[PDB]
Structures are given as C-alpha cells and as structure tokens.
Length: 130
Length: 142
Image 1: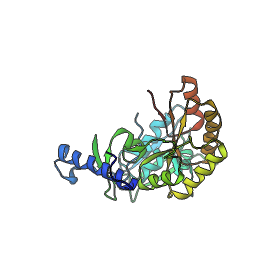
Image 2: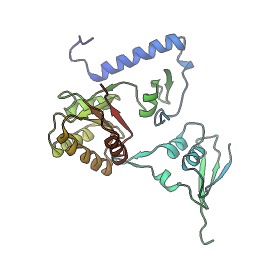
Image 3: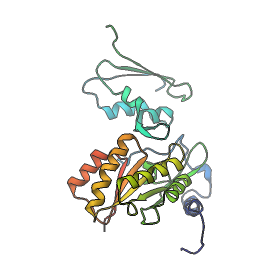
C-alpha cells in the first residue's frame, strides 16, 4: 500500500480514518450521520438529578464520589470531575478541580441545574469556624 | 466498533483505544530513524494522530530532552505524544526512564511510553506504571 510519494501524514491518516468511517456508516448506520451519537467531547474514558446534594465521609469511595459529581451527561462538569490532567500553558498537570473536591468528612456539594450544562453550578461547602 | 461525533462535527471511530486517547484509533509507532525526527512527530500530532518519538536515534538524555522540547514547541496547545524505547539495550532504559519520570514531574505531554523488542518483567513494568505517571503503557509483545 506504499505507492504515492510525499503524501502528508495528515492526508494518509485522514484517508484511512474516513475510509473506516464510511464503511462503518454504510454497514452499521446505513449511510446516515444523524444516527451517530453526539457528545460534548470525546476522550478521557478509561477502558475499565437537577438539584443534588452530596456529602463526603471518611469511608466514601473517591471514584464513586467523583462519578456522582461529574454526572451522567458528558459536559464541562464531566471533564472537570473526571479528567485526570489539565493543560497548562503547554504542559500537563493534575486536575485542580479533582484535588480541591477530593472527598473528606464534612464536605457538602450542592449541584444546581445539573440538567442544564450552561447554568449548572457546583457549590462545595466545608465547616468554617464551626 | 462504533461511530461518535463531537460538537465540531468531527466523526471519530469510537473504539476502546480511541475512547481512552480522545483521538482516532490509529497511531504511528516509534520508528528509528523515522519518528526520531521532532518535525515528523510534531506533524503527526498536529494532524491529530498518536505518534511515538523513538529514542533509537537519541543516545543521551540531553539529546532526547532537546528533541522533546522541539516537539513541544512545534505542536499546538493541549497536544500530546508518546515516547518509544527499546528493551534490549539496558543503557537506553537507564537514561530514558529517569528522563521520562523527570519530564512527567515537570508536566511534559508524554501521554505514554511504548516498550518494544521485549516485554518488561512484572517488577519493571510496575515501576514504570507507578513512577512515570503516564496515561497508559504500550507494550509490543512478540
């Protein structure tokens, strides 16, 4: 298959990807892109309620806590509470949202307008001065 | 395998590897001397396809660091690439694995480490997985 010379890597890989996409669309979607599911962003998925109030305890499981805070629908909240790394100026560092929202006794997280991603607000409260 | 799309409308082949990496399930493996070039690695990453900077053309941590810095300068913001190392030469590992750990400590976009020409033992693989703090570990069994 190595015939055409000086074809850019972009062109070669895009050709392979569009070939796979076209064949998959023809076979298991019926040549209809509307049948393709849509998500806000695609990536970061490991191979392995409008108004909600969550409480963190000593024995609470951190992964379940972060999954609950992220929610089911894929959005900025999902990325904030499940993406392991954030992008610095050009560098990759741990997720400050996850580090801040790490569960512990006394933390109460109130998620308002969870259904609407645009208006969703997550408020974490801790015991301060009692 | 399935198909998925994002807000921009780009059609992705939803498959386990693609879901993990947030990119199409096609990658350019570490190739000495082909992927040695920082320009080619940066070009593939800008194209949006996984690629491994092969260490075979680098014999020193300083040289590989210069190449990685060149790749980082050439790629766009938020981009990522892997590093490929050969297991048959212990010198390669001795100068590369500490370098990968140091660059990941600095926060470099080293998405993964691929090990070719041999599968590391359980202890060595565990040490890589724990210390390097990579997104995933590639292994090329024979």
